Amino acid sequence: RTTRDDLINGNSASCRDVIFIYARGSTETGNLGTLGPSIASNLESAFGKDGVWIQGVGGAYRATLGDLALPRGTSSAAIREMLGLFQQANTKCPDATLIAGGYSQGAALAAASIEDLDSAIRDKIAGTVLFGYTKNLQNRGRIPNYPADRTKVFCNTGDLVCTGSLIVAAPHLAYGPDARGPAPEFLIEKVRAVRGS
Image (cartoon, rainbow, N blue to C red; front, side, top):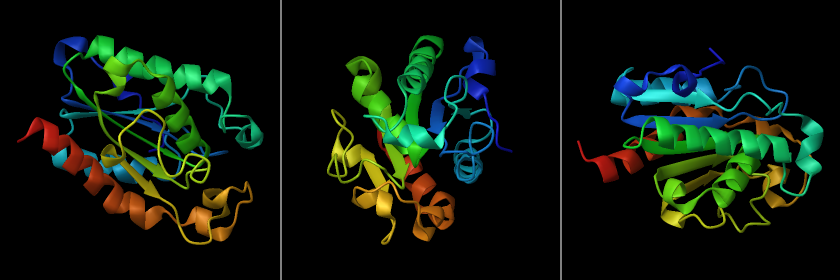
């Protein structure tokens, strides 16, 4: 379903090897929204249920549509909430490999959080996927301070938010197939590249 709090609920004595932190789009439900569940089920198939913890960004992140217009594409409160989850993962499970993702406002949130994150923690994020990245043009398809090889952006032709606008057109709502195949495929490949088998 749309709410997963595996990191918050998880036991430090039995940490998963992989922790996925994901931010939903504006007005979406739970803490995973429309795309998160599809990615989650595929990660679970590859690493097994006890092998991966799925954590959505909830709490202070209310995914308010109007916040897309703020300087960083989301609110300060939301960034602090996502930063807190990365810090929680790092303290709770020091040896877990992290992966991240975000859709629309959540993609701006993921980018802002990763930019502000302490380098020692940021460097543990093996891969990040962004769908309908609202700061795609502004950041030239990159996440500041984060390697291009660990980044995968899914920006549909005709998705105006990828070209510097805040208009929501039909292509912005067409990332379903990407969340079902290429996105988890990329995340799995990036985790295996560093963890092996």
